[PDB]
Image (tube, coloured by chain):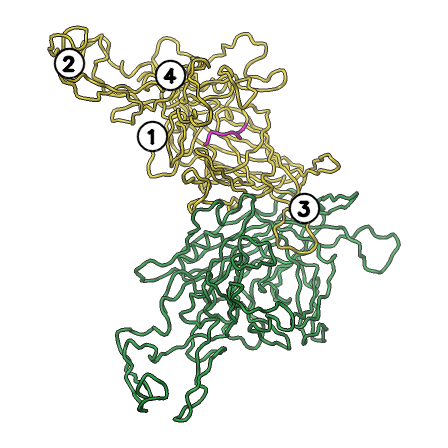
Chain colours: A green, B yellow
Amino acid sequence: DGVGNASGDWHCDSTWSEGKVTTTSTRTWVLPTYNNHLYLRLGTTSSSNTYNGFSTPWGYFDFNRFHCHFSPRDWQRLINNNWGLRPKAMRVKIFNIQVKEVTTSNGETTVANNLTSTVQIFADSSYELPYVMDAGQEGSLPPFPNDVFMVPQYGYCGIVTGENQNQTDRNAFYCLEYFPSQMLRTGNNFEMAYNFEKVPFHSMYAHSQSLDRLMNPLLDQYLWHLQSTTSGETLNQGNAATTFGKIRSGDFAFYRKNWLPGPCVKQQRFSKTASQNYKIPASGGNALLKYDTHYTLNNRWSNIAPGPPMATAGPSDGDFSNAQLIFPGPSVTGNTTTSANNLLFTSEEEIAATNPRDTDMFGQIADNNQNATTAPITGNVTAMGVLPGMVWQNRDIYYQGPIWAKIPHADGHFHPSPLIGGFGLKHPPPQIFIKNTPVPANPATTFTAARVDSFITQYSTGQVAVQIEWEIEKERSKRWNPEVQFTSNYGNQSSMLWAPDTTGKYTEPRVIGSRYLTNHL
Amino acid sequence: DGVGNASGDWHCDSTWSEGKVTTTSTRTWVLPTYNNHLYLRLGTTSSSNTYNGFSTPWGYFDFNRFHCHFSPRDWQRLINNNWGLRPKAMRVKIFNIQVKEVTTSNGETTVANNLTSTVQIFADSSYELPYVMDAGQEGSLPPFPNDVFMVPQYGYCGIVTGENQNQTDRNAFYCLEYFPSQMLRTGNNFEMAYNFEKVPFHSMYAHSQSLDRLMNPLLDQYLWHLQSTTSGETLNQGNAATTFGKIRSGDFAFYRKNWLPGPCVKQQRFSKTASQNYKIPASGGNALLKYDTHYTLNNRWSNIAPGPPMATAGPSDGDFSNAQLIFPGPSVTGNTTTSANNLLFTSEEEIAATNPRDTDMFGQIADNNQNATTAPITGNVTAMGVLPGMVWQNRDIYYQGPIWAKIPHADGHFHPSPLIGGFGLKHPPPQIFIKNTPVPANPATTFTAARVDSFITQYSTGQVAVQIEWEIEKERSKRWNPEVQFTSNYGNQSSMLWAPDTTGKYTEPRVIGSRYLTNHL
């Protein structure tokens, strides 16, 4: 519309309705020029870290974390009152564009606003580009609305053959300029809308019943079983008579059951006390990567991280495994720490009702057929696939964690739910790409056909607004006694938690999940 | 609309109608960047000064004083001709926005206007934020229309537990960016409207009658009373006979009366002559805070300041108490003075008809039941609540004082009128918040997820207009002789009072209240 006319307004709120909540949040961004306006191929030959790909001049908006869209109070309203959550619609606006040219002269930089410069924006609706937005990486909106964030650079990997960097003829190059874009000056604004495909509600609740306890504790089964092959409490001694008996109440472990616990992939267990662990190197002949549970994909090890949902130790427990996500705590110098107390550990232990424990076996199975001569042998089940009549609970969604993921495009998928967390989507929210259009510097007066390298140094800033409509289930329980709630128990604090400190810094003190209200199997 | 098109006009006038006056005033403001765009928590552990809270990047418009909306002549038209005043409607405009970027280079600052920068403005209509606008503090429009004022920074306290700074889980953090705002460039303008809830007229008048004199001085009552228990003028001597008598005229003190004087909280009295006061420290073991009348709220002393309305010494009298408001006079160095003649003292003495004196007791009450053996004992009433059949007069509104206050949100309130002065409102005029939107400085070329600290230094200026509709009562008295008026008696002056001086400085020479015209009980 105009230079001196604002192209949008600031909107950040949540509005709660009967069956739905609509959260809006606005942020301020700054977009640098990446790679001097030019694509660059990436790669390194590493034993398991081997990768190859392309970094692009473009940058993109990552909307996928829950604290982008929710405050800590709104997250409390949600999880305390509701059994389920799923996203419905999404809407995005990019407005109040400002492009700034900078001038380095006489050892000092001055910034002026270039009014005729443009910025390019397109959302990829057809999913034609590699989708990196679900990778669980950085570059999303800040949790706190006053923060200004930097738009992350876009890049993508490609199929790696073995442990060697080198590309083959299968590798694709995608040129972002080969899509149609929208070019925006300071008067122009961008907008798009999106609809989520129907997806099961995330279950925000814990079970108040175990699987193996689903029976009536008063009654007996009409089913019989073999109690023992001999008299006495000692093995391989007795009168050698087979005793059959009815299954009476009080001895549930022998009840015949309709269902089974969920699948397992065992994890290696580590103690938070440093002296209580076996000494393992970070890198070398024996890596910690070797001793963790990994999968070999094309001669490349990769952790199973978290892996299939499995019950975990409590957040405060003195042991952890890779089945637990780890977030930085309130006070961290960054990139390293020697103490687990600085870290904030996730725990799935609420799902211990239906699911086997990450660091413990699924069960034990007979390895032979006994006879009078041969004693029975059983053995541990470390990894178990799904079986008919098996039930399991998904991993929990967190306030700091990802909302969705893109289901890979493949001829088969089983229970398409993301192992980090959230909502598997075949057509997730489309990636929105933005770059500063190049402005050439002063050209030569004669003609040359070499591409022009010299460019005016610029960056742009602006405002971005996101609106997601969510759909929620109200808890409908006949439970008498009070349910557990998410409360602030933090007590007497010199400086308020979940608020800026004396220096203005805002951090998130705790990891908070969605499962508080109980329900029954 | 446009860069080179003005978004509003200058309007300052009052327009008087039969039952109403509509005053408009326009000012020029300047808005700095506060706290480098970031919230900061505040607090200090003090014995009674203990506080905790948050200072915000935002700033706000304080419209609450009378001289914002009135000139000294308009204030004279009002109070001389009218018994009552109440506000009706209010309207606010913020226009002619100008955002200026500043550059410090080579030891000198240059200012340029950034045309694509925005400013954010929202009024809080739902009273969701802490309301600091009624606190009787600085940061309102200047009295004199040529002055340019600086928009005050916004901040708020929180519930303090005891004498300790530390917050508890009850303390709230409010993020202003979590409201919807309006973003304005130089072409854009802001506007809002507001309606006052029905409120009793402030009574601009003094009583021409005392309570205890409401009788007919000619007649006698038909009521009798006990005149004395003995003969003679000396106590505990006489003939010990009970004498009853009719209540004759001329001895009014014994008249039976339908009504009582207003409540009291006694104040400590101080003489303006320094030698005539008892020596008390400002701070130490014995504070002057201890010896003034205070209330203990959660182990924290606070003055009763002014407190319930009570008659006071005259403005020129040689003694004062905390029941009298104090304003700076025409000539003050600021923040301190050793002489009361520099200060301008408020006086409530007009209400001495219905109200007890601030430094004197409500009365005296019998402490025992006398008999022949025991002499009667009475004792002073320093503090008295309201009683059935009690009448009182509110504190006066001044030209320099607050217009309204927000009635706290609580399950009970008694006679909700602000003890400083003005109009108690449940939904007062909403606070209007304004800040400079951040413009990031030159970002790094690589990507980092830390929030961007570096910012372009900016400020904005503009114009703000306020229009309040007022409702007034015309005096309707049958009084014969002339009433007291507010006149300029200042006499021969080298430099005109109520006008700028030779140096351009404008001050307010006197404290002027609203009560001149008499009325009768």
- The chain carrying label 3 is B
Q: Where is residue A24 in the image (x, y as percent from the top left)?
A: 52, 52
Lower position in the chain sequence, tag 4 or tag 2 = 2
Give the alpha-carbon distance from disc 3 to disc 1, as whole Å.
54 Å
Query: Label 2 belongs to which residue?
Result: B226
Lower position in the chain sequence, tag 2 or tag 1 = 2
**In front: label 3 or label 1:** 3
Give the alpha-carbon distance from disc 4 to disc 3, as whole Å.
61 Å
Q: Are marks 4 and 2 on the same chain?
A: yes
Q: Does the magenta stretch include residue B192?
A: no
Task: Tell me whether the residue at label 2 lies in contact with that at label 1, contact meaning CB atoms closer than 8 angstroms.
Answer: no
Q: In terms of secondary structure, what is the magenta stretch mainly?
A: loop
- The chain carrying label 2 is B
Q: Is residue B140 magenta?
A: yes
Q: Are marks 1 and 4 on the same chain?
A: yes
Q: What element carries label 2?
A: strand
In this view, the residue in front, A43 or A315, is A315
Q: What stretch is highlighted in magenta?
A: B135-141
Give the alpha-carbon distance from disc 1 to disc 4, as whole Å.
20 Å
Query: Label 4 belongs to which residue?
Result: B350
Count residues near mark 2 (Cα–Cα under 10 Å), then give few for <14, some for 14-19, many for 20+: few
Report the residue at 42% width, 65% height from top. A350
Query: Label 1 belongs to which residue?
Result: B415
Report the residue at 74% width, 50% height from top. A457
